Length: 109
Length: 109
Image (cartoon, rainbow over the protein chains, first blue to last red):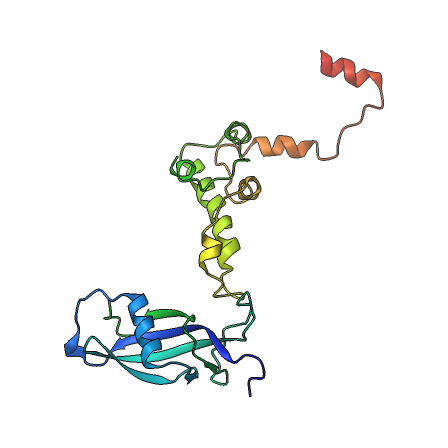
C-alpha cells in the first residue's frame, strides 16, 4: 500500500486523562512515556485518528494519534510532509520522534 | 549583552557601524530593532505555515544572528523624529551631474 514509506519517523500523540477524577499532579517524563509506548506496542501499524489505552505506572490514559509522519528506511532527513489525512500509515520503530501534546482538557502535566 | 556572552552572535557584526546608521533613533527604538533582527533569525528555522514541523535539535543547536538580518530589520523599524530628513534625501533622487565647472566652485564655497 505505502510502497516505500513503511516506518514511522515522527509520531504525534495527544495524551489525555480518561477519568476526570483521577487527575494527578505528577511530573511525567516524555522519554519514559515514549519507552512505555514502544515497549507495549512495537512494530505496530498506526493511522491518524486511531485511539489507544495506556497504563503507565497504574495510570490509565487516552492516546490519540493526531498526525503521522511516514518515512522509509535510509532517509537521512525527514523531508516527508506530515499527513493529517487518515490514509497514511506506518510501522513503529524504537527511534520515532514521539511528541506528546496536552489533551483538549489540558490536565496532563 | 546576554546574546554575546551566550555565544549566540555571529562574529561579523560590528556595533560601531550600527550606531552610525541609526541617526535619529531614540532609546526605546533600538530594542525593537533587536527584536526584529532576532525574529528574522528564528523565522528562518520555523517557517510558520507551509513547511511546518521542521523543528529539530540540529537546527536550534546552531542559531546565530547575522549582519544582514539587521540590515533587513532597518526596513521595519522607522524613526519618529527623523521624518523631515527623508524629504532631503529624496530631493536629490534625480541624481547629480557635474556638467560644468561652476557647480564644483559653488559646493566648495
